[PDB]
Image (cartoon, grey):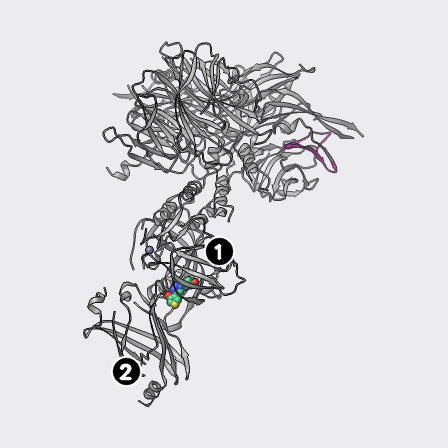
Amino acid sequence: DTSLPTSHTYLGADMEEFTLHDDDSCQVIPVLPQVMMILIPGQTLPLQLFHPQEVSMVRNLIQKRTFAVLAAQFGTTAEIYAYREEQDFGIEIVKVKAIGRQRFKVLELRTQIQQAKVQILPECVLPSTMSAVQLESLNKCQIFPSKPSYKWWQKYQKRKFHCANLTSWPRWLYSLYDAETLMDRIKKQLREWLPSNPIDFSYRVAACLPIDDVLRIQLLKIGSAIQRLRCELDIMNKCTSLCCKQCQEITTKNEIFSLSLCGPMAAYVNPHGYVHETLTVYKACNLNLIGRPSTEHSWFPGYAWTVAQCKICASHIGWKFTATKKDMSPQKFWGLTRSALLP
Amino acid sequence: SYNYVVTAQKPTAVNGCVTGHFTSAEDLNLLIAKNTRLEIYVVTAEGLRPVKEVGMYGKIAVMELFRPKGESKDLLFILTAKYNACILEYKQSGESIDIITRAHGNVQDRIGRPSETGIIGIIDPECRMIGLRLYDGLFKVIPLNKELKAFNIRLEELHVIDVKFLYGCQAPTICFVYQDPQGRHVKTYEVSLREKEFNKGPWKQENVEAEASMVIAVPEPFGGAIIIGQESITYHNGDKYLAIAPPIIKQSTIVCHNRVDPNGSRYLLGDMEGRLFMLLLEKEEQTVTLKDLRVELLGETSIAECLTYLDNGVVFVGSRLGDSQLVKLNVDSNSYVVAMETFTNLGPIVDMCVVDLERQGQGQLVTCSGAFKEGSLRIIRNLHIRTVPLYESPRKICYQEVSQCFGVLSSRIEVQDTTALRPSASTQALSSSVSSSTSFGEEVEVHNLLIIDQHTFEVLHAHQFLQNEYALSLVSCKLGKDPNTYFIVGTAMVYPEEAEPKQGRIVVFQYSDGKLQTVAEKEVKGAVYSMVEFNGKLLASINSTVRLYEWTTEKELRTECNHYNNIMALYLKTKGDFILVGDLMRSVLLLAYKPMEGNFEEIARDFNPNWMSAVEILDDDNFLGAENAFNLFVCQKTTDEERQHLQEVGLFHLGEFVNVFCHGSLVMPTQGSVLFGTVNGMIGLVTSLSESWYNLLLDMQNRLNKVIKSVGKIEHSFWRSFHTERKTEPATGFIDGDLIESFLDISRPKMQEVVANLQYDDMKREATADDLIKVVEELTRIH
Amino acid sequence: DERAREILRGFKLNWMNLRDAETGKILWQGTEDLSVPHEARVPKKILKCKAVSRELNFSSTEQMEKFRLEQKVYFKGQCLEEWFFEFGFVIPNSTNTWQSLIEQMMPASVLTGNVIIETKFFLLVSTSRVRLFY
Ligand SMILES: COc1cscc1-c1cn([C@H]2CCC(=O)NC2=O)nn1
Ligand SMILES: [Zn+2]
C-alpha cells in the first residue's frame, strides 16, 4: 500500500518513539561514518548501526538525540524518531529511524566517529513578494477562497499580483517567484509522472527528484524556499531519463511513480547495515534479474525483492519487487539506487 | 563605500486619507498620508489649503483621527510599517506650528509573521482604545498610557480580512470578516479591557460571500456593519440582515470607502477601475432601523486607494495609481463626478530617463508614471512637473537623440469579444501599425511601443505587438557600424498555460521619416527580460542566458556568446566592460565580457536571498540595489572567494519601494548622480561621497538626531535601519539627505547646539554654523 | 571428547550461500558439509565487493550451549585475515540459519587456489579447511 513503506516495518514494529535548535547557532554534533547519502530536512533516514563505535555514539546521542549526515561541504542534522536495540548474534545492533530536521555547512571535522563542528543554516523564509508594493486598500483582496484549474490560477494572478503594475515587472514574473504558483507547478509536473508549507514541501520534492549528488548538495546549499523550488522545477524540466553510472537507459522519467508518502524515492536500509536511496518506478528496462523473489526484510511489505543489474556492464542498479498477492496495487514495480544511476 | 540618499521629489502617491477636526474643533481638515509624508490640508470652500506638510520617519501604514473624552480637537493615531505607533496632537502657537507627540511606542511583536491581509488598524468609536491586526493570529490592543503599552489578544481565525470597530455598543466590539476552509464568515468579539480578552459578540458568525473582503462599521442610529465583496453587499446588525447584488459592482472589486454623512445614511465607495459609487442607506423609523441598501454609480475618477468626503459635495479621491484628485459629486449627473483639482502623483514610476529636452545642459527627467487609465509621462525639471496622459500603463521608456522622440512601452487592458476599454495613447496614435511575424470578459493586455515626440508629446506612432507578446524591456541605441539608431524591444510571448515563457523576440525598430518600421527581429527561445547597449553590441537577457548580439552588416542580429547563470537576468546594467546581472532574488552577479577571448566570465557573485526591485552600477566598484522591504543598499566588488564575492557594504531603509535607477542629475563635493523612482512617486538621488564627507555627515546625523525631535519621537536610526521579515540591522554607508537638508530649517540656536564641539576639515578645526550650513547648501545644490 | 564426536556425527551443513552484502547477488552457493574435516568454487567477485553476507544453514542433532565459530584466512600458509562469529543456543535435531559478515586483499590471480579458509565450529566441535578457487 501507499503507507506501508513509510514506517519501515522491516526494522521491527517495536521502537522507542520520541528538538528545535537555535537558528545559526553552531553545534558540535556527531557524524556517523556509515552514511554516504545526502540527506534533506524532512526525508526519513533509517539506519542499522552495529559497529561498536557507532552503537556507543547512538547511545550517547539518545541519552541526551540529534546527529548529522554529510555528503563534505554541507549536510543535515536529523533527530532520532525511533530506537531499537538487539543483542542477537553477540552484536549490539541498533536500528534507528531518524528524520532530517535542520541543515548546516561544514566548518570542521573532528575525530574520536566524527564530531564535526557545523553551523546551522537558518531557514531563510521570505515574505510574500507583494508584501512590499501591496496597497493598503488592496490588502483585503489578497486572501482567496479554497482552491476548487487554469481559471483559478488566472484569478490568483489577477488578484494577488494586481499590485505588480505598481512595480516594473509583470504578474507572471512574480508568479515564477511566487511560492504558491511554484507549489502548483511542481505538483502538476509530479502528478504528470504533500505539505502546504513551502519549506517542507520544497525539501520533500527535493527528496523526490532523481537527481545527481552534485545537484542535490546544490539544492541543500540553497537557503530560501523559492530559490529551491525554482531550481527543482528547472531540474524536472531538464531531467529526461536515468542511465547506469557505469554505462553512462535503465529507466525514463515519466515512468516514475510513488509508492510511499515520502515520494518516488526514499532511504531504505540493507538488512546488514547499508543505506540505499531507492527510487520506486513502474517501468525499468535492460535489467537482468538475479535471485528468486524473496520477502526477507522487504522494504515494501507484501512484496518480494530480486536483484536487478543492467545487462550492459552487469552493474547492480536496483531490484524488482513482485507482490506476494495479485490483489496488491500495483502487481509489481522496481526500485533503483541513486548511487548507481546517472541522470 | 559611502553614499548620500536625498529626496529630489517628495513622495506624491497618497497612501492614506482621513478627514476630521485636527487643526481645531471648527476646522475640517483632510490629512493625507503621502507615504513618508503627512499633509495636513485644511479644507475650505474654495479648495484645499496647505497648512503643514510634516515629514514622518516612517511610512504611514495606518492613519485615523479620534477625540478622547475631554480632548478639544481630534488626536491622530499613526502606525508605521515598521510598527512605530504614535498618537499625536496638533499644537499651534502663532506662526510657530508643531505636532506634539502625545504618546509613542513600538508595537512590534518579538514573534509572529505579518498578516497577509495587511496592517489593519482601527480606533474604537468611543476612543477607549486602539485595535491593530498586525500579525495573523493576534490582535494588538492599546488602551487609553504615554508609552502605548500594547497587549495581544489571541484570535482563533488566522485569516482575518477586514476588521472594524462597531458603533453604539455598551463595550467595544470588533467585527471581522475572516476565512475558514468553509469560506468567509463574519465574527464579532466584544473586547473587554479589564479582562483584556475577547467575549462573545452581539451577533455570532454569519456566512457571507466567498469574496466578502471589506467591512465598514456604521454609526448610530443604525449600527451594525456593511460588508462588501465582488458581487453582493450585505449589512448585519443583530437579527437584521439586508443583502443586495447590484449588477454595477460585479465589474470591479471595491477596495476603498469613506463615510459621507455623520449619521451614516450615505456612504462612498471606490474600486480598482477608478469607478466611484455612492452606497445609500435607506432610513426607516420604527427607534431607527435600516430599510434597504442602494448603490449609485457616481462616476469614474482616479484609481483610488482611498476616498474622503470633505464637505459640500467635495470628495478627495486619494490615488496611488494616478493623480489624486478633488472631484465634486454633482447633485445632477453630467456622470456625477466633476474634477475640481488634480494633484500631481508621479507614482508608480515604472521606468524613467534623464534627457536634455531643452539641450541647456540640465537633464529634464521623463518618468513613466501611473498604471491602467492613469498612465502618463511625467516631465520633471528644476520642481516643475508636466503631465502627459497616456490612458494606458506605461512600462519602459527610452530616448532617441536623432529622432527627437521617446519610445514608451505601453500596455492597455482589452476585453475579449478584443476591445479597448478607453481611447488610449496607442489607439490615438497618428500612424499605428500592428506587428506581423480565452472567453468573453477575460482581460488581456495588448502591448504597444508608442513613439512620442519630445516637443509636443503627440503620440507620433504606436506599434502594437503580437497576441500575448508582452514587451518586457526596451532600449534606444546605436548598434555596431550602423549609423542609424534603433528602438530595440525585448519581448516574451506569455500564454496563460505556460508559466515560464518559452518564446520571445528581440525586435529592432527604426523610427525614420515619421514611420516606425521594423528593421529586424530575432526569435529567441525565451523571455527577454532586460536589455542594454554593451559597447555597441547588444546585450540581452533570455531567461537564464545573458546573450550578446552583434548587429551584422546585413542589418540582422547574430548571437555572439551565452552565459548561463542559473538565474534569469531581470536586471542588466553595464559600465565599460563590467556587466551587472541580477534576478528578483537579489542574485547580484558581476560578469566581465573579455574582448580578447570574446566570452563572458563571472567575476563576482552574491546570491543572498532577498526580494529585489532594481539595481545600478554606481561605478566600477559600487553597485546600488533595492532590497525587499523598501530598502536601498550598495554592494562592492586577496582571495578568489573574497574577490569573487560582493560585500554588502552600505545599507539603508529608504522607506519607498524603488522601481528604477537612472544615471543623471536634474541640475546644470559628491561624485556621481543616480536618480531613482518609487511606487510612491518619489524621485530620490544617490551620490557617492568621500570618506571625510561621509564621516562629517554621519556625525551630523547623530547630532541632529540628538536635537531634532521627529513627530512620534521615532528614532531615526531605527527608521533607516535595514528591515526584513527576518532581519533588522542599522544602515551603513548611506546618509539621510532629508535629515542633513533639514539643518537649514531648524532654528539657529538649535543649529549652534548641533554644530557644537564638531571637528570640521575644510587643517581640522572647530566647526561653526555658517561653514556647515554652506556645506549642506553645497549638498542641496546636487538636486 | 564424546560430545564433540556426537556433534560431528549429528551436525551437517545443509547449504551455504555467500553473496555480496552491498547487492545480495549469490556469488556462490553449495551443499557440501563444510564442518567436516575440501575445495569451494567461490568466484573471484568476492575480491571486488566491500563485504560478504554469509548464510550457513546447519542441522545439528545435539544441542550447543553456545554455538560459535572461528574463521581464519591463509595465503600460502601466511595468515591473511581472521573472523569470529557466535549464534548461541541451539536445540538438538534443529536446523538454523547463520547470517553474518565477511569483511587491501591480494589480487584473485595471486590467491587463485592459494587461499585456505580454516573454519572451526565450537567446546570445540570440529575443524576443517576449504581451498578457495577464485
Ligand atoms: C545484505 O544483503 C542481503 C543478504 S540477505 C538479503 C540481503 C539484501 C536485502 N536487500 C534489499 C533488497 C530490496 C528489499 O526489499 N529488501 C532489502 O533489504 N539487499 N540485500
Ligand atoms: Zn551499467
* Location of residue B179 in the rendering, given as x and y in whole percent from the top left corner: 61, 40
* Residue B601 shows up from this direction: yes
Q: How crowded is mark 1: few (under 14 residues within 10 Å), some or many (20 or more)?
A: some
For residue A260, which numbered disc appears in the image?
1
Residue A18 seen in the figure: no
Q: What stretch is highlighted in magenta?
A: B214-240
Residue B185's x, y, as percent? 65, 40
Residue that carries the numbered disc 2 in the rendered image = C37
In this picture, is B69 found above or below A256?
above
Q: Distance from label 1 to label 2 (Cα)?
A: 50 Å
What kind of residue is marked 1? Answer: Ser
- Viewer-nearest residue: C120 or B164: C120
* Quarter-of-image position of residue B74: top right
Q: Does the magenta stretch include residue B216?
A: yes
Q: Are marks 1 and 2 in contact (CB under 8 Å)?
A: no
- Picture layout, residue B418 above or below residue A118: above
Residue B426 as seen in the image, left or right of residue A93: right
Q: What residue type is labelled 2?
A: Pro
Q: Is residue B109 above or below residue A290?
A: above
Image spot of residue B235 (x, y percent): 70, 33
What kind of element bears circle 2? Answer: loop
Where, by quadrant of the figure, is residue C90 drawn?
A: bottom left
